[PDB]
Amino acid sequence: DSEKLKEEIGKELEELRARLLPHANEVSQKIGDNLRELQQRLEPYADQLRTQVNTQAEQLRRQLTPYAQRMERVLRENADSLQASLRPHADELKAKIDQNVEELKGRLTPYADEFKVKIDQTVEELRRSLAPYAQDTQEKLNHQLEGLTFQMKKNAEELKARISASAEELRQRLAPLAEDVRGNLRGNTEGLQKSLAELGGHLDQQVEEFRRRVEPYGENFNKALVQQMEQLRQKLGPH
Amino acid sequence: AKDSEKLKEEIGKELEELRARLLPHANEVSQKIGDNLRELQQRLEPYADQLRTQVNTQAEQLRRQLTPYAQRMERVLRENADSLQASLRPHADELKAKIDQNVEELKGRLTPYADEFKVKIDQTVEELRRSLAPYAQDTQEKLNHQLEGLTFQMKKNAEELKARISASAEELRQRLAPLAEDVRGNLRGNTEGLQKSLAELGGHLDQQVEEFRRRVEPYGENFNKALVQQMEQLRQKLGPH
């Protein structure tokens, strides 16, 4: 089948060779000549195929390379544009932390001041109710009551000071969170996103620390003033 | 030591004197102080209560005022990511399209050479037949058949060259297309990410194009070699030994 149709090729070639046998040298020479002519004919095309491989591969690069170049440029321009768009909001956050901590402070300190008013009102009434019992030694009564007014008001001033010092600690704890976000405008989008996704949580933790610390103050000082007045009652009253 | 007791008795010396004056009324005075202490509590209470409330209300207001900044910055960041994706997508789509279009242009400019080899084979074999015919008289049919067989074997090598050029242009296409696909997949949701694929893109295109160029460059000479060996085989078979 397949082996027989290979023998036929050999057989026929052997027969052609047998016919050409008396001219084997001439025939070998004519084949050698045609082989050189083949090489000469194929040569410019074999050479140009190699050149065209290099020319085409080069053309394909010159055509495709501008796309990566254009996309690299869009990416850089965008990163600049993003930074320019984000910076104003990052500066406004930093500014609002400071402005809102002062507003918080300013809405809390009036209470400490109002305590000073209620101390004055109460001591003046105490003086009026104690005056009939010390009509000749009113100087001593006044001095002792002025002394009490001072001691009581010093507690109201301490409340105001502790509120202010705690609002300031809150400011010094919130400001770095705004700096961290601002520092990440320069750098990776992931770093910026992590600081932005975590910002709210970190603000809460710090605000909660302030609220936890300042919340007891009002009741604490109310009891302090009461102790002061109760101390006077026990000192001046019966044994 | 123990002189704190001495110091404590010096400070309240005037208070001891005020007490000595109030002594006959100690009960009345204690009562009037107790009354004022209740009035004090009553007066301080709403402010002490409101201070506690306001601490909570203000701390909450600070939180609500600062939160929109992280929210606005997240919005600027997403609007930008949308804008970047919309700016990059046209170029990303055009790169994908040009890879395919330019690989076909490349293929179509290289295959004509293998076809031209088929022309040069025909010309050469026809000349070989003309130069061998005087020696094979009454045997032209054996000569022609053997030369047709040689023409076929030689042209099958030219057709293999055309096939290898096409298969290599296709390997180049299958190596360049994923680079465009990878970029096209990183346009949004991954920036670390897209920044890496974009910065590396040009370099990766070059490496693949160079691999094609390096593989296909020897082909022409290799095939030329093969045709020569075929004609040399005929010379050795038909010649003296």
Image: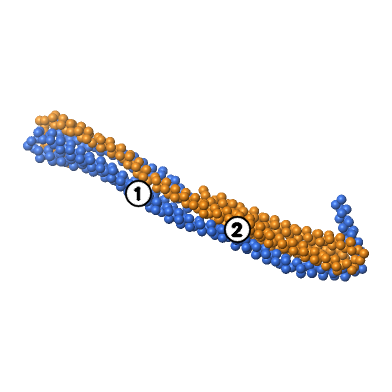
Chain colours: A blue, B orange
Which residue occupies 88% across, 53% down? A4
Q: Is residue B60 above or below residue B200?
A: above
Q: Residue furthest left?
A: A136
Residue at the spot of label 2: B205
Q: Amino acid at mark 1?
A: Lys
For residue A232, side relative to residue B183 (left or right):
left
Residue at the spot of label 1: A96
Q: Residues within 10 Å of mark 1 (few under 14, many from 20)?
A: some
Q: Nearer the viewer, residue B182 or A182?
A: B182
Q: Is residue A27 above or below residue A152?
A: below
Label 2 residue SS? helix
Residue B5 in sight: no
Which residue occupies 58% across, 56% down? B95
Q: Estimate the spatial distance between the alpha carbons at disc 1 and disc 2, rounded to whole Å.
A: 49 Å
Please report, as a chain letter, where disc 2 is located. B
On whether disc 1 and disc 2 are found on a single subunit, the reply is no
Which residue occupies 80% across, 62% down? B230
